Amino acid sequence: AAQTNAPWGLARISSTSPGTSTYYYDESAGQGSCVYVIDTGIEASHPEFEGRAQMVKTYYYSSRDGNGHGTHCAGTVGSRTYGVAKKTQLFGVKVLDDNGSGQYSTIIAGMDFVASDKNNRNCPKGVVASLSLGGGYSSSVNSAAARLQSSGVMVAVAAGNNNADARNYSPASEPSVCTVGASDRYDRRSSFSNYGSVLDIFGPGTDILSTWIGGSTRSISGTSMATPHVAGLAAYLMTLGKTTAASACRYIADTANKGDLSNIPFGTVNLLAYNNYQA
């Protein structure tokens, strides 16, 4: 399938070269997979989600996304126009308040929620969790992410936006999950992207168009935007049967575009997420 005039990041993940604008992908499109977006919520009523999004849990007075961040990330995972995996099921877990903040204890509870809640959902092709959040190093936060991964969920987490080594941030620094840095449309490391040995992969993160609250759209930047590209890619590849939740991060690294990014510090992987789809 070909989506013309796609957001640059979608075109990038199906291309061996920057500078194109059509996204190419197998029409299975993540059907039968599920992606949990653990964030500020999801505006499930947005036409772009086509009834495939729902809120499953909140720790606050509403499950609505009063911020936009979670809706934007969910749109990159799975919206019809802005999403990588256009037929996946999206499940929102609101661990962040409408200002985008959340206590680590709530975030940990949300991760353990997903590890159990997947047993209440129909996801025959597999389960992914996208975590566009983080703070300073916490062994308890890392351990929660490790448990979620161990339970059979492909966990993708943001590297962070500090232009620093991600070893000092959580859950970015957890070795067993997929830690995602950000790149721009010219294949440069995004100016804010964290780096370091703990990163597994880069995805598009600068000037990413996606859904927003109030039935709208906007372009924003962050490792928060790169993470759902990788989460959606995992769901797409799992639906294709090419990999599993336990092996998808490694498979994405195996099949990535290699050595094409600039300003990657010595010791950080130079790997850009790529679907290897041959139309």
Image (cartoon, rainbow, N blue to C red):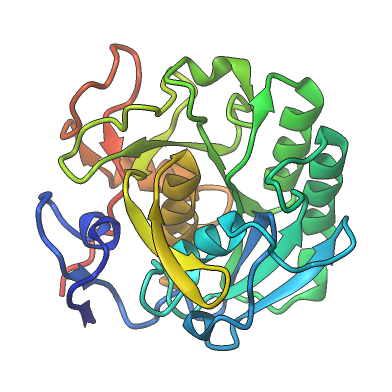
Percent coordinates x, y for residue 210 in the rendering:
42, 64
Residue 109 visible in image: yes
Q: Is residue 232 above or below residue 121?
A: above
Q: Is residue 174 above or below residue 227?
A: above
Measuring 25% from the left and 41% from the top, which residue is drawn there?
A: 184
Between 82 and 245, the residue placed more toward the observer is 82
Q: Give the left or right position of residue 278, taking residue 75 as reference.
A: left
Q: Quadrant of the N terminus?
A: bottom left
Percent coordinates x, y for residue 31 in the rendering:
50, 80
Between 179 and 58, the residue placed more toward the observer is 58
Percent coordinates x, y for residue 108 in the rendering:
82, 40
Measuring 48% from the left and 54% from the top, which residue is drawn there?
A: 228
Percent coordinates x, y for residue 158 in the rendering:
53, 38
Q: Give the left or right position of residue 177, taking residue 185 as reference.
A: right
- Residue lying at the far top of the rendered structure: 266
> Which corner quadrant of the image does residue 43 belong to?
bottom right
Q: Is residue 268 above or below residue 178?
A: above
User: How many labels were placed on the picture?
Assistant: 0
Measuring 76% from the left and 66% from the top, which residue is drawn there?
A: 118
Residue 238 visible in image: no
Between 215 and 49, the residue placed more toward the observer is 215
Q: Quadrant of the C terminus?
A: bottom left
Q: Give the left or right position of residue 20, taking residue 78 as reference.
A: left
